Image (spheres, coloured by chain):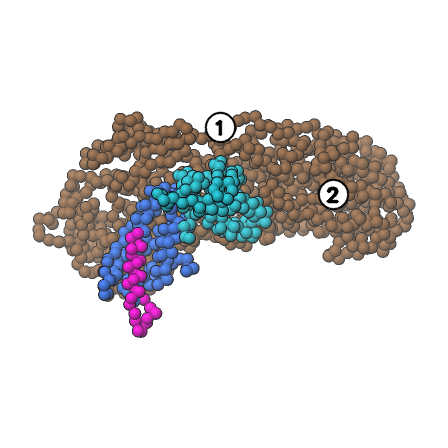
Chain colours: A cyan, B blue, C brown
Amino acid sequence: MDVLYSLSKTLKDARDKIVEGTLYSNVSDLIQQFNQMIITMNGNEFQTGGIGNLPIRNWNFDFGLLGTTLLNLDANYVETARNTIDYFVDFVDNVCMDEMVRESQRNGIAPQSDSLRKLSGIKFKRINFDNSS
Amino acid sequence: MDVLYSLSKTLKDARDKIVEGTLYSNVSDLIQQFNQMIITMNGNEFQTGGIGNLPIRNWNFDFGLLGTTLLNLDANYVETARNTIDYFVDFVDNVCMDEMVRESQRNGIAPQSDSLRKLSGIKFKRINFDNSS
Amino acid sequence: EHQKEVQYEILQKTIPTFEPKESILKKLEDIKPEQVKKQTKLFRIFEPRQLPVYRANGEKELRNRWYWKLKRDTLPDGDYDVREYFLNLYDQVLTEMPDYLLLKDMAVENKNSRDAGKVVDSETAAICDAIFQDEETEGVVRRFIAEMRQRVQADRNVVNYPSILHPIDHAFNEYFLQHQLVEPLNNDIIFNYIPERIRNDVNYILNMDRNLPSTARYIRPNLLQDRLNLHDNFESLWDTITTSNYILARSVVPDLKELVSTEAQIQKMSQDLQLEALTIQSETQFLTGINSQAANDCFKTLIAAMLSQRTMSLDFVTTNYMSLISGMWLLTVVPNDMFIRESLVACQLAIINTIIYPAFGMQRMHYRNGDPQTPFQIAEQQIQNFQVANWLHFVNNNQFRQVVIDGVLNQVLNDNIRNGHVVNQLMEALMQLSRQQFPTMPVDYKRSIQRGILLLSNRLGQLVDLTRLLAYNYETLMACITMNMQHVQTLTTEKLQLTSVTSLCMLIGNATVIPSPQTLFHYYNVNVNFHSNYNERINDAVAIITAANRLNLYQKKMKSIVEDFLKRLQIFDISRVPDDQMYRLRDRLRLLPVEIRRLDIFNLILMNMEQIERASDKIAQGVIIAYRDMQLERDEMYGYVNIARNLDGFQQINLEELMRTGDYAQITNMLLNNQPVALVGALPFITDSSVISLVAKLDATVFAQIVKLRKVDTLKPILYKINSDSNDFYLVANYDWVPTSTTKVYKQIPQQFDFRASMHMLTSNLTFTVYSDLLAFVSADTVEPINAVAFDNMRIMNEL
């Protein structure tokens, strides 16, 4: 679960600190964290939806990392990034919603969805960070 | 006083950004600040309470630091850390409460408690940090 | 011309440019790649030795507890000297920076125990066998040592070997593992380290031949950009770079081929030229020769100039009008933008005047420029022959389109598709010429002039070819430049005799040459390394300087580091670096981050700094005087001694401060009216066993000194290692009594040894294979020259 959290603060602190004109070094510590993610992800496939009117969309990952040789970003840098973020956003939305509908009497304190159950897996823990929300 | 502040944002941004898994280079800038503290403290004795129904608990300092090393964090790393945090938490609580009751006609704007008066000392100033609250 | 020299040189002393031309090339091809420093030893700082221990009031308790001690304990005297010492460690750390690591290469037999055990390194081994036998070591110890077996996983490449280091040691070696700065390697990556351009340049063939184990591993090249904008002030050094980058270029620029026999052309030339026809100033237009060379020189020279972002002038020869015509060629192409304003000055006006204007009949008022807007341009507004008129705007506006960001950050001031191979420019440069045939002055003039012009025109069918050539070449070579390149007015020129120019011109046939594959790479490779070195040293530099500041080393900082820096860069010979330059260089350096690597380590050293210093055997931090009979304390290790683990209750006087700043005797008064006081910092040291001594109150002596000599180096203080043994002086415990030390010291006690906590496990990858050079794996051929093509795709060099 905590996993999930990160995924976002990652994107927020991303769609926020990554803009046309900021010095690289203001995101050095960040950039890293990001990439680290892409890696852990790529390869594994997911299923969301499959209930009521909720659509069953299939997500797959195949992305190239990010920059490393930059000094204050050039517009071009952003757009090639934003394009990658938007797939994760539209993703998480579907992930949240899918686990935001399932309920369980016995153990209704743990992950239900096929999507999240897979995240609590150990091979992902490598992402968690900045738990200030 | 401002001193006090830090002590917390230190712990919060700590009990928050230090979780099983995260990448070190997200806390590099943090870890440091932390240690710096332990140092300044170790070798000091404090005392809180003494008024009304407020217990008089005593405190001492003598702690080891933190490996800086490791790409990612292993569970073991956390627990050995959390154990040290919990002593500071239970500390500050007692510190706050002790200075949160005393009032002074004269300088009701200055520190009161034996606990805090000692903090405004210069040798502790080396701990200030991130005043955004 | 002697007067010209002295000064032309007084300038050259403000240029860290090495002397000979060639002498520079070597320095580059030479800049070898950074040696990797795989590594053997685990690396520590301290092993644990046995030591005698005497219980309170006791003799050698017979036991010998294990304590940690420093291998190589060389600490200076004085807080300041200490800070400097550590600093050297930083330098040592960096020079030994193990880029990667493996453990099999350190395997060792854990002599004892049942499951074939192979522990980390030699020291790890020793220790085990050692303790195994110190009979007073909990049954759990042998056990652990015993059964603890390595961890070998064939698949995945994992190796977890049991080890023993130390808190501060694990500290190091650890990060060294977590920063193996070694990324994988797939055919695809090699393919990719190739300019996004070349691959698409048909003329060049690509192919793979060798495979790649999942064992493949390389080290990032690290090609950050400029970081340092030398483009706006360090002229002296740019000139030196340009020069360099320039020679480099010539070394590459392919030599030409298939030219027209020198003799043949010049001969039809005399027929056409009508040389000796009255005109007094003969045989100045034919010093043109040695063209079989001049062209090669003019050619090379031209490229490098561009690439290297150099700027030049022209060994111009006013009379020789022809030589001028060709000039027009030059501007038709080479973006005047990079030509010191002046040499262009002469050139144009020489054209403008002794040409066009009068032979064309226009301004018979010949002309008059100042220094702003150019004779080649303004002439426009005032010309009526469209053809003529287009040349003008195009020539005055063809600004080497200083705008490019290709294949990932490579500002390489580019050039017009037009020019490229649209060429027409040439066709138009000609058409305009095709209608310059008319009156004004003597006959032998137009005759001679126009006839020469025609030789440009006919040949024009070919002159085209020239355009294409360069177009490609520059447009090619360039691709492989990492260093960015802002256009700058170099301080130095480069002479280009219209002689050669003119030759190249009417003297090139259906030749067709291009950069040999192998050639190209070699080029990349170089700039690469160089870069890597620049960037790297930069980091090495910064790291130090910053450390230099918190490490309060208020001394070297200026030059010191800078000197070494430049030297390693090779390219230039310091010395002739104006002083405003070296310092200014720091001014810029000090304002940058720090490669995590570098930085991350210093942060570590500082945290343990304190601990080391007191950990040493010789030297403690300051002493105390109380002129109050004091009770000697007792510690298991030193026996009966006068140690104080804490100041508090007595002023502190930074020796460092005092010594460095002279004394005001504040101390002199306190000592004199005999007052409680403390001294802080690192200090000499003295042990003594003379029970008697204490009685003689020796410790209250040494001090008086200081005042006479105004110094404080000679301040050896005293300790009384009074063990209930090694002290012949023991008529002490035989008499009821207690130690009356008038003084004691700060050296905190060494650390006890606790196995458990020093035993760490080890995460190490397993079995690499490091590759350098790279490229090599690339198989590449080349079409036959007669079949080239540019962006054009029709065919470069196409006048069958």
**Which quadrant of the view contains residue C531?**
top right
Q: Position of residue C455 (x, y in %)?
A: 83, 38
Residue drawn at (66%, 28%), measured in percent from left and top? Answer: C782
Q: Chain of mark 2?
A: C
Q: Is residue A28 visible?
A: no
Q: Residues within 10 Å of mark 1 (few under 14, many from 20)?
A: few
| Three-letter residue code for mark 2 | Arg
| Three-letter residue code for mark 1 | Pro
Helix, strand, or loop for circle 1? loop
Q: Chain of mark 1?
A: C
Q: Position of residue C538 (x, y in %)?
A: 50, 46
Say which residue label 2 marks. C418
Q: Position of residue C683 (x, y in %)?
A: 30, 52
> How far apart are the alpha carbons under marks 1 and 2?
47 Å
The residue nearer to you, when weighing C533 against C465, is: C465
Instruction: Answer above or below: position of B122 versus C22.
Output: below
Task: Specify whether C448 is left or right of C222.
Answer: right
Q: Position of residue C13 (x, y in %)?
A: 59, 49
Q: What is the span of residues highlighted in magenta in the rendered image?
A: B86-111
The residue nearer to you, when weighing A126 against A27, is: A126
The residue nearer to you, when weighing C135 against B106, is: B106
Helix, strand, or loop for circle 2? helix
Residue drawn at (36%, 41%), measured in percent from left and top? Answer: B74
Say which residue label 1 marks. C213
Mark 1 / mark 2, whichever is N-terminal? 1
Q: Residues within 10 Å of mark 2 (few under 14, many from 20)?
A: few
Q: Is residue B97 magenta?
A: yes
Task: Specify whether C157 is left or right of C254.
Answer: left
Residue drawn at (27%, 34%), measured in percent from left and top? Answer: C127
Give the position of the C terminus of chain C as an image quadrant. Answer: top right
